[PDB]
Length: 290
Ligand SMILES: Brc1cccc(-c2cc(NCc3ccncc3)n3nccc3n2)c1
Image: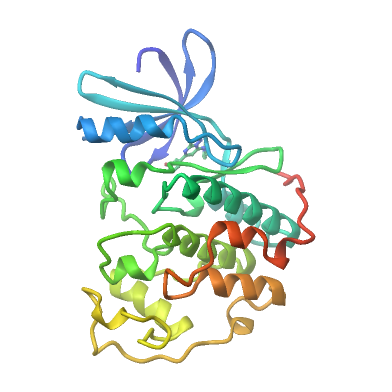
């Protein structure tokens, strides 16, 4: 905390304020995250993340716990995907770059998932990009450490847009499939230049999902009608063709996206199988203009 000079507020994250900072001694530029409460379970979970190192995962440099306050020190990246998508609304991200980013994000997932660590709150705001054509996932593993609240510490609404349907339907246990759902929602958003499912409450989110993909049933999703927040009185909507949902996307893309958005989490494609999908046959790594 005093080992760091604040350079600038980046924003108010899920768990606290996020700062760009400089290591006062070493001069290293880092992202400093304050985690508002701390519990031994959290400290032990966090420490395990220091080993979860991968080029597509923002590096956890240190955990500082002093005076019952908690700070996480990460590798700093200059830009996130949400700002990048906004900045390129006029023209859209070129497909070769969307493809490269999707490819790298799936690599990040495949790595963490193989160590059985989930993100659970993937969203454009925590996908970070550099001037080298790289993209990295920020805040991996934190949801398991600190929970995911409804409001941030500054009362901002945590988005539901990328939340998997099994969460919304009140599953007690999350699998890695929840991240593949979020990431498919982001893939669709990069392609169309519009969020796929911009829900503004849990039921609005669910009902937006049903409107596009069909109200799930026992045929598409064995066991769905027995989940805690499922109701027989949900309206029954018919599925739309993906040709209509993500129009410009080619047949490989639409086929991969559909597998990433399968209702049944057990059927939803894994990150590892997604990397082998023919969509990625001609993948390259362009530099974004930035
Ligand atoms: Br607020 C908020 C919510 C979720 C993630 C981040 C965030 C942003 C960046 N940098 C992107 C950025 C930097 C400066 N200004 C805007 C965005 N970094 N870099 C390392 C971790 C990290 N976490 C910030």
